[PDB]
Amino acid sequence: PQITLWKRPLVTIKIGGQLKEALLDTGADDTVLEEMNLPGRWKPKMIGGIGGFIKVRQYDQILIEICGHKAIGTVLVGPTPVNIIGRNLLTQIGCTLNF
Amino acid sequence: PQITLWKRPLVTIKIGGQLKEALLDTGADDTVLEEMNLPGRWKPKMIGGIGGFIKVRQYDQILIEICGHKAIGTVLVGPTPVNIIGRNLLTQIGCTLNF
Ligand SMILES: Cc1cccc(C)c1OCC(=O)N[C@@H](Cc1ccccc1)[C@@H](O)C[C@H](Cc1ccccc1)NC(=O)O[C@H]1CO[C@H]2OCC[C@H]21
């Protein structure tokens, strides 16, 4: 669909069989989700934004459904105040910015 | 234009008569700019991000040109690592997400 930016671009995602709200965020290089249980081996990582950094866990080749579009890629899990779908998965579902 | 997300969506903006690099960021409610000399009245304000909060200077009705399209709205200046153009101005240049 076509998403306007008058409100926050919140969408429904499906990950590990659970449904959640996430923000589609062109300013995020990677996808970061509120704390959750994910399968697989994982590596530590720090992501930085306004105000500093947070320590997160990097899971690889994770399946995630974003408004019906399937994606499989890196998903970070950590103390983010908001679920963010970043450019690594936005490119997979074919998303572009247009003005 | 149509902007893909394989790389960071960096664009050139014109503000206060100066040209700068900024990130188009659908994940940001507001526009936050690197520390810079801008004339006019401003009010102090606190904004929150992924790593915590920062004190910023809130300028109101500041004119800003982004790839030729004009926008006027609130512009915060503060210790952000990167210039971010938020939804407050993205909507004015008529920007949307499409997948
Ligand atoms: C996730 C990730 C992984 C790997 C690399 C990077 C850079 C990543 O992105 C991190 C990241 O913070 N990006 C941001 C942009 C950026 C990029 C580079 C360095 C600094 C900031 C942004 O786009 C997402 C952020 C999410 C959010 C945080 C707290 C509350 C609500 C939403 N919004 C944001 O702080 O907005 C500000 C401004 O306006 C206000 O509205 C709402 C919040 C206020």
Image: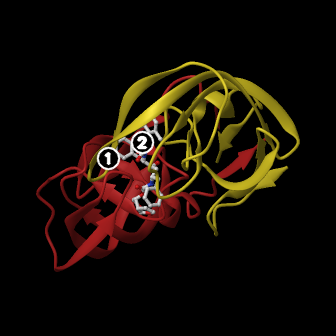
Chain colours: A yellow, B red
Where in the figure is residue B58, as x and y percent of width and height? 25, 73
* Quadrant of the rendering where the C terminus of chain B is positioned: top right
Closer to us: A53 or A17:
A17
Name the residue type under label 2.
Leu
Chain letter, disc 2 residue: B
What numbered label is drawn on residue B83? 1
Between the residue at mark 2 and the residue at mark 1, the CA separation in whole angstroms equals: 6 Å
Where in the figure is residue A63, as x and y percent of width and height? 76, 28
Contact? badges 2 and 1 (CB < 8 Å) = yes
Q: Would you call the spot at circle 1 few (<14 residues within 10 Å), some (14-19), or many (20 or more)?
A: many
Q: Indicate yes or no: mark 2 CB to ligand 1 under 8 Å.
A: yes
- Same chain? Circles 2 and 1: yes
- Residue found 63% across the figure and 40% down from its top: A37
Name the residue type under label 1.
Asn
- Residue found 18% across the figure and 53% down from its top: B79
The quadrant where residue B39 appears: bottom left
Q: Indicate yes or no: mark 1 CB to ligand 1 under 8 Å.
A: no
The quadrant where residue B73 appears: bottom left
Where in the figure is residue B98, as x and y percent of width and height? 76, 44
What residue is shown with label 2? B23
Q: Would you call the spot at circle 2 few (<14 residues within 10 Å), some (14-19), or many (20 or more)?
A: many
* Quadrant of the rendering where the N terminus of chain B is positioned: top right
- Residue found 55% across the figure and 50% down from its top: A34
Q: The residue tagged with tag 1: helix, strand or loop?
A: loop
What numbered label is drawn on residue A15? none
Give the mark nearer the N terminus: 2 vs 1.
Answer: 2
- Residue found 85% across the figure and 49% down from its top: A1
Q: The residue tagged with tag 2: helix, strand or loop?
A: strand
